[PDB]
Amino acid sequence: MGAGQTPHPQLIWPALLKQQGCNELLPLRTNDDWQRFCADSKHLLQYGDKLVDSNFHCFVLEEDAHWHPAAPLPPEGLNDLIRAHCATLGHCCTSKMHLHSVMDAIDFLNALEG
Image 1: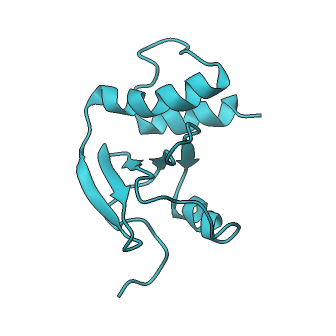
Image 2 (image 1 turned 90 degrees about the horizontal axis):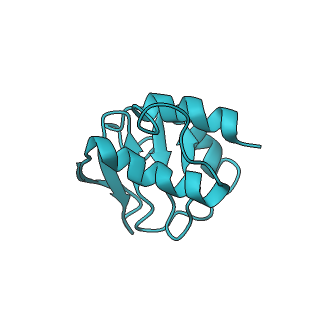
């Protein structure tokens, strides 16, 4: 029993999805941005697709179409995600240690993308 297609209630938006095999971080400003996924493509999303929230909770997706808590994350472990989205495009920082936190990432990725 659950009343929306949401990843986890305990995930505090914004969030950062990093799909299996791909590298493009999926910034998601809020729960609307996630609903805009299944609204527009009920596809993708492997058991393995990883989510991270603003509180550095990692999650992994299961075949039970839920997200399980897959440990908290170090300050550098956010950088381990964004390492993909940056390297797949061509970016390597612009002052400070790439990104302070998830807030800063969602600010960055907007102004990057084409």
